[PDB]
Amino acid sequence: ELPPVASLKGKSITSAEQFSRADIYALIHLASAMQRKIDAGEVLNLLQGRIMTPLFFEDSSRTFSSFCAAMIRLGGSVVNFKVGETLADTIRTLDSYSDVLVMRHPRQDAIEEALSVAQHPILNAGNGAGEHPTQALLDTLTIHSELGSVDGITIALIGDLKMGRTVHSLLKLLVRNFSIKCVFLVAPDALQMPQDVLEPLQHEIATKGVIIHRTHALTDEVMQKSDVLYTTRLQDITIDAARMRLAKEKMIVMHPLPRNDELSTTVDADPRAAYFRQMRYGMFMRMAILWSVLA
Amino acid sequence: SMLELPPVASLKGKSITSAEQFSRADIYALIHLASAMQRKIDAGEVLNLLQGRIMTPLFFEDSSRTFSSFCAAMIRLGGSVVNFKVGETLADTIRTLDSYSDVLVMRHPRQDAIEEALSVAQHPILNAGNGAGEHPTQALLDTLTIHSELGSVDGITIALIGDLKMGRTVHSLLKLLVRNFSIKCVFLVAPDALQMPQDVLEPLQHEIATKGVIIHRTHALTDEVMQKSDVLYTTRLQAKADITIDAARMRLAKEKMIVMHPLPRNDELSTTVDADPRAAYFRQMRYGMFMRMAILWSVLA
Amino acid sequence: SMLELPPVASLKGKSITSAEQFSRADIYALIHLASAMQRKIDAGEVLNLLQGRIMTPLFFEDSSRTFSSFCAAMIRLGGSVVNFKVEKGETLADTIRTLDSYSDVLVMRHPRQDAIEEALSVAQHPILNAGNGAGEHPTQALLDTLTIHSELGSVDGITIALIGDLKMGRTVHSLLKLLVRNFSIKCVFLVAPDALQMPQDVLEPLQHEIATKGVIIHRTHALTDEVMQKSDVLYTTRLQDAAALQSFAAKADITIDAARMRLAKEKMIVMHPLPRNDELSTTVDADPRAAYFRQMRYGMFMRMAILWSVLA
């Protein structure tokens, strides 16, 4: 079966904060059941005659495609709305004809604006520097499916943690819902994990017990102890073939993409390079989210 | 369901280019077909009617709402859509589309582009806006709106407000209403430079005469116009012409009336009016998907 | 409908990159499969053969016309399309890997001739080459062969002229390779200004097969009465500022119009991959031997036949 996760039915998907551990577990397992079927040649007509509409004020072919492909693989349909008309006027236009909106916008508070006037679910595909929860959830699914489990892991977050909307959402989702041992906040000092992200996290950091061992650049303590390396762009941070020596045998590298120098192509064929497999997990997590919300 | 949703027969095979081609019988037949489809789609049903047919948009002009309304119609009837983004002539572009398609939705800035396309197309064309000419589907959904909000089209007093000279919406709505309905009065609210052209109004003189329809121009949105009108149908001006509709002017209006707009909108339609139960212009978009569902199915059945 | 629409088994899982990869039997397989498709679609019937399967574009040129012919074939097979726009300097290889994550087949068009060989090297899914610089347009060559076969009854025994910018024409590079290697062409006329003649690196690799089958090859720079009165197929292309593209006399010499068509035989066809400029007069359009618009319908059925066979 592919029963939907009941608690998302009709819900908007704005923040990682809204997802309980039972929620995550269920989506992780719906996504896998789905992968099992798609990989087996099965066709899913779960969402026929239902329409998703992207509302991408900023371009991103990968995020766009992944949502589309996911909707299509559930039998659903896609109608692009290329984007001065006010945001609300657009939101009401999409509500005319679609069942679910998917919005990517450069201002953080554009999301809260839209939800005030929206009659159908809005899925947040990302907003300025705040969040990007379907990424956080797809990243967790990657880890669950690559390493066996997410409980007890050590995780490194490389790159500018200030602007990177993937690292915030992930940091919240993981700490709040799992038993994370350590978290290497690796970046330049100026471009680090903001105070407002780290502050609401402080209850769980204590009672679970969670080492936030920061670092200016990629130390060997990181490479040695990390089960997951989650690097990002910024446009002694590079992960290359040389440095990968120091990694354990059961670990993975991740990157949401796109990339620059900070992750060498010299790592691509390494079986612990999970950054490409991560995108396919993405399609499957979004199929699980789309079915759950629109069921 | 060929049972519960029977297409309009006059439309089968036909290109849809002007208001002039629709009879009054056709209009109510479309309106009833639209409503039957709204009940079926709102019940959560999946219509399978145009499985394997392809709709191909051909927009030589930016218009996301029109495109998406049309794509949404087609899809909810079970049809498919092929995106074509606009040296190479118009005819050749048409003959190309024609090689894999079941219906074309064209939207061009030049007025005569439609005659050019029709001259060569083998599959039906629906005109989604041809220069300063017409927008026949818009006028058909606007009429569905009037009917579904007010319960009758005969006897209304209507204000066409804004750029009347270049508004392909208002050209089509005026033609559609005057020709096939007993319109009491029509306020032509606009500056003299943006007035309703005489070659839209000439062909109607005879029908205007017979049905006894008052044709009244004002350069500004007066209080007579607000108090008498059952539909205020407003449009943009793409410095100081006084035609704006806010919540204050809405104190002058009747209780049973609607405000309408094809969209997008500028300063002529304040967001103060939105909450008002007589603000129809958001419901107008939804009605439009169902009329377009009605039309597409009728064209292609 | 798998005894109704049998896929060409030799093509299963393959990327389609070059015309040289096809045998005579393959081509006839695809023609017969494409005709069965026209029978299905023209009967008003619907197909589910690629339900659930996704095609995406990896287009670095822009040619909506071509991505649309492909979309249309995929959609009529019951399949689906996810668009993907390319604009950054993110690597070609990463673009491929990102498409691979959710697609079942890629349709590639790149202006560099040898970006296809890069994609193949990293792709885990079949790539359909929809044009590579001055290289090949293989699907195009296959639908052109289907056209000729449908309209004249057979391909062996034809005289055919290839007109226009042959140096850069990729449609003609592939059509020439396909025709000469698998059919007994009576004669190819290469009609083009000297600077834009069919390249030597295309012709030299076909010399054994020419010599052996006795194909006659005549260059000209003009549509001489010989060409018009002997050709069963007039395959012209478009010119893309160097001396020959600039010359009015180069244009007038290769142009087909109502006038020149008076010299042509009762039973032949005029073909063009589209789009066209002035080299093919709109005065030829009414002529029943103008097969360039029908060419587009054959093309849909030939892409259906190719995709069904790659993805079955």
Image: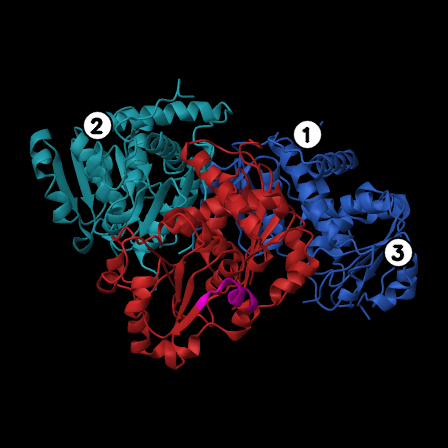
Chain colours: A blue, B cyan, C red
> Which of marks 1 and 3 precedes in the sequence?
1
User: What residue is shown at x 30% (from left), y 66% (from top)?
Assistant: C278
Q: Which residue is mark 3?
A: A226
Extreme-top residue of the structure:
B3
| A286 relative position to B106: left or right | right
Q: Which residue is mark 2?
A: B24
Measure the C-alpha gap from mark 3 to mark 2: 74 Å
Badges 2 and 1, same chain? no
Q: Amino acid at mark 1?
A: Pro
Q: Secondary structure at mark 3?
A: loop
In which chain is the residue bearing label 3? A
Q: Amino acid at mark 2?
A: Arg
Residue B56 visible (yes or no): yes
Identify whether B30 is placed above or below A131.
Answer: above
Query: To which quarter of the image does residue B273 belong?
Result: top left
Q: Magenta region: which residues?
A: C208-216
Residue B269's disc is: none
Q: Secondary structure at mark 1?
A: loop
